[PDB]
Image 1 (cartoon, chains in turn cyan, orange):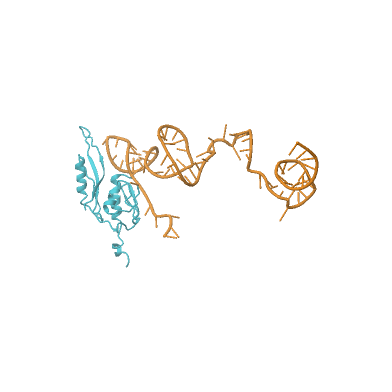
Image 2 (image 1 turned 45 degrees about the vertical axis):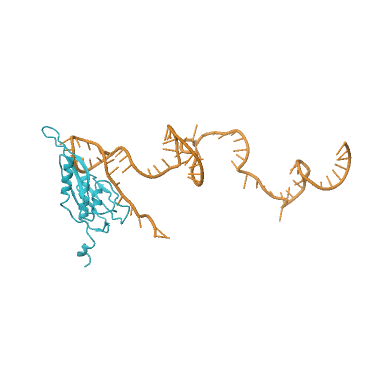
Length: 150
RNA sequence: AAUUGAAGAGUUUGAUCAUGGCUCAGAUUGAACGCUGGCGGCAGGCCUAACACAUGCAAGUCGAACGGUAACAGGAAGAAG
């Protein structure tokens, strides 16, 4: 049920007095298959060290996303840093058809149908979080019955 | 029952995030060239010189408009081997 996966890994540099020392950072997103979306970045001097902290941080900071059946309740716009993310429900249509960075967050959230097409900046670390912000701000037709109806 | 569907990647820097061009994955064509090549069905086939042309053919048809025997097909009459 853990359903965890990595998006991408990127080598970086420091350049201290002695010379260049290269660290590694692996982005990861996790989910239970029905809502409960979460993610983690982290860093380390090794590849297996950095991925471990990413999956470790992905356990905490997990929030529910509301879905109808196996689809979104409505289309929702979301932005983060310099990235701009749109999505459409498209009920049982073709499905989970999207490029890397945003592929992980949709499939692990539970959606096997919605279309992405992420505009603006397509940076792996900025394109993620635009989903979680765009899925957190999304509200549910059953639980908006507080404002709706009466 | 009927225009119900939306992907990204690479590259500036010691490394990073924007901005921003270039490049690639797709489909398509009245196509060509390179290499190769079994059959069938359907469709397509001078996109440049509206440059110029050999030869045949590409529009004739009515004797039930009319005077007519020029053809060969008979019939009729005549003259002969």
